[PDB]
Amino acid sequence: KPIVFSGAQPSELTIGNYMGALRQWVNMQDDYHCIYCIVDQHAITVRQDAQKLRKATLDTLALYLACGIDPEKSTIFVQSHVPEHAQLGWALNCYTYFGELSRMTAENINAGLFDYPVLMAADILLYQTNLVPVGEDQKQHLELSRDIAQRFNALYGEIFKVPEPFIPKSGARVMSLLEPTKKMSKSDDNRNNVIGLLEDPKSVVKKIKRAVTDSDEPPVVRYDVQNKAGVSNLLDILSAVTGQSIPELEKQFEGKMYGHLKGEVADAVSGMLTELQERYHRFRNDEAFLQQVMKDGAEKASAHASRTLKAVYEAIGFVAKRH
Amino acid sequence: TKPIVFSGAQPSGELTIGNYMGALRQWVNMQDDYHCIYCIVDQHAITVRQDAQKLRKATLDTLALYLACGIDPEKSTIFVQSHVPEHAQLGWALNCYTYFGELSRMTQFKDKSARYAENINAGLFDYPVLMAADILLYQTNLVPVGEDQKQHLELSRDIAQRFNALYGEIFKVPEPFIPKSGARVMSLLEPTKKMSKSDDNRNNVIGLLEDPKSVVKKIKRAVTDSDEPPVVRYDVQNKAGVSNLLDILSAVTGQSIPELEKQFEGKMYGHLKGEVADAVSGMLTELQERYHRFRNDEAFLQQVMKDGAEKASAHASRTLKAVYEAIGFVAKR
Ligand SMILES: Nc1ncnc2c1ncn2[C@@H]1O[C@H](COP(=O)(O)OC(=O)[C@@H](N)Cc2c[nH]c3ccccc23)[C@@H](O)[C@H]1O
Ligand SMILES: NC(=O)c1cccc2cn(-c3ccc([C@@H]4CCCNC4)cc3)nc12
């Protein structure tokens, strides 16, 4: 099976993240050898509270498990638990141009923020990764990892796989509630633009009722991204939850106002989130379960990572460690 | 417990009398007085592009040379840097508490970048952070180095203090131990330039594993000055070559420069060079005699690397545990 590497930040998922990327990938765990790395060494490139970082790491783990990531099928682990990432990160620094890092898309910036694309390259290249499902803002980073891999391979032979981006997209388009032109993003400042995965039904109703629509008279529930962006987003959200087609929903809401739509959207979304939240809290509060998932995952990751790093170290010419 | 000494040298190029006087001499002298840990920094070496066979051989050459100088594996911890993962682990973590401007301003990065314009790599830029990690892992009190590493060591103090201010008494703040003589041995044909272990012009350098007869010839041809009459006196500005020779002689014999100046009263550069050649040739003969006994004994070198990496890992893992707990990582099971 092809190896898929996905990096997960320990810092709050939305329905866009879930119904888009994550739900798609939960259903492909038997098609691919999927690896999920909670990237706590990348997280510290921004200064943050220590106790919140620890909490956020475990929050992220439980939520990925809640979404359906199966630790017996896929490998899920915490980045800092596998030393090989930092080890390969340093080695690949020596085969990465300073220019390449400076050209990524002043003197008080920390070196971690400057140097993390190399660590990212190491994260991917450690596991002989075939595919990486990056977003558009990390396409440049993946490309650097491909360039590093080909450069190293040209000097020393075929040590690394040249990874590819995962090209086909989720299916669910999920846009911001007060800005339906812009995509719903976990990193949005405006909280009223997003529905978080742990939001309660009262919070969901409030945010959906405030969601922007249009001034059509009569109000008409019809799909039109150009002219009716807000109503179209509500339709896409509802379709993504229920599996009902757009033309089916258009018929279902014939002669109905935007209030009825919003009510059904809120009910559908919160119906979905109640099942995920049940799973989330059950997993998250079970310390022994989470510890065993992390230990098992780190063990699997380390077995593969050590194999690659040993070949890298042999190629460079380092004297092999005496065990 | 004793205060801790940490220092390192690269298995790249060929170690010189400069590397010896600035660093290795002090390493040997500190072994009983302090708890000493000495590293072959192969991960730093590859910031300049190395042939793979040369790197491996040079790592083992350097190890054997530590032993030849008098570094005793019963007294000191001797290990190869890449054998202890914690160096790279703390190296990454400390990037996040190091500013970009602190690294771009470094003299060594600037010198090496001008020299290797075809390979100005991220490792060469990030060099000081990994070096800080090397030191800070072992709760280091003293770092014996030459003058050229003072800037790097100052940053490691800054990183230690900056991290400690946020998180508590995680690191010791290390101090430089730079010698009075031989802290910056200069090139024989260009005494305003530091002696390099990778000089294109071999006549500039006195190599630790070089034929003593070849070394004597190079000392004889070392540039001096046009002073009339020739006078053996210390003056770095106007008599760089003579001063450098006096410095080398002071560091080998343990005699002060004022003492040497008095000794060479009424003498000229023939006496100076004769005395420098005698002392250095004697030193290298003894050193190289010991070197081959160690270097050709693979079982012994293998055992030193095994025991050393074990000792180092015990200390390094303890520090990294505390660093990881402080910054807020979920602790490994
Ligand atoms: N011409 C000279 N005269 C006097 N001393 C000199 C001369 N040239 C070099 N030195 C000193 O030799 C030591 C090793 O130098 P390296 O370039 O191998 O290697 C270096 O310059 C270090 N970055 C290696 C290192 C890596 N991590 C560390 C942690 C602590 C101490 C040292 C290290 C150094 O002490 C250096 O000051
Ligand atoms: N997104 C990925 O699939 C991925 C795979 C492998 C390594 C990765 C590292 N990242 C990543 C690295 C850094 C960041 C940000 C960069 C800006 C500061 N805060 C953290 C976000 C994501 N993403 C990775």
Image (cartoon, coloured by chain):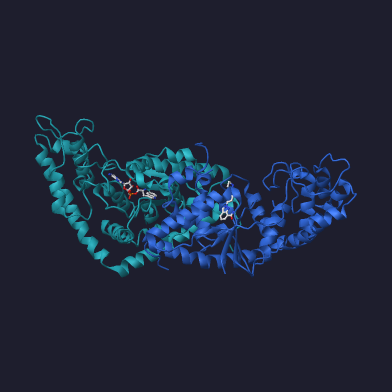
Chain colours: A blue, B cyan
Left or right placement of residue A134 versus residue B173 in this view = right
Name the foreground residue: A183 vs A271: A183
Would you place residue A155 above or below residue A117 in this image?
below
* Residue B38 visible in image: no
Quarter of the C terminus of chain A within the rendering? bottom left
Measuring from the top left, give residue B120's x and y in whole percent: 39, 45
Mark count: 0
Measuring from the top left, give residue A181's x and y in whole percent: 71, 43
Q: Quadrant of residue B40?
A: bottom left
Name the foreground residue: B70 vs B285: B285
Left or right placement of residue A210 versus residue A190 in this view = right
Measuring from the top left, give residue B267's x and y in whole percent: 9, 36
Q: Please name the residue shown 74% across and 41% down the image.
A: A179
Left or right placement of residue A254 versus residue A106 in this view = right
Name the foreground residue: B97 vs A255: A255
Q: Please name the residue shown 52% across and 37% down the image.
A: A108
Left or right placement of residue A172 versus residue B228 in this view = right
Measuring from the top left, give residue B260's x and y in whole percent: 17, 39
Quarter of the N terminus of chain A within the rendering? bottom right
